[PDB]
Image (cartoon, rainbow, N blue to C red; front, side):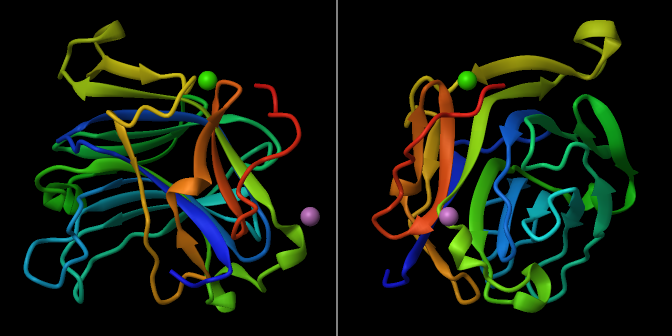
Length: 241
Ligand SMILES: [Ca+2]
Ligand SMILES: [Cs+]
């Protein structure tokens, strides 16, 4: 509650089991920063039992021309991971891109602008038990070894989310016999608190406090902000998509 910088974490109030998730966005990048789009079983992090369930897309500000895919299963203190690296062109902070995650009982699939960059079948996928919510966050890590020196002269930084679409898993049903049917679309003309929640917390390793001030709708785009506390409001024009 006392750090000098603020960041963001947006999360769907409801979690689901299987589905397709798409977010049209332009990311923020700078040495030290981290932003991800990820499926997440809330409570996975609580040492008291329960498996860890998570699927990530993560962009490290020091190299916006690339991102990592990952599946984390197991349980805190014995989690299995599968970090892979992928290229993005143009760099995630120079243009809008459609990032997609697909999760069925048999495979997890990652896509950018509707093109596949990874598909995992079986294995860890089998241990993605229960539900997961859809999350997006923007922060800075203290581990310079992982994210790079924290380039403070670069703040304020802003990520822009134009829209999100969430589809249900309907094996065979859906266009061209695909496995998903559109459930809902959020074009972000407003922050819909009946659908989304904003984090208000932090952790050891996070140079920033995630606060509800760092997420807000502006000109038809959702904005996630990384800035000095009190400086969360964007000035200037929203990038066009
Ligand atoms: Ca929009
Ligand atoms: Cs600046």
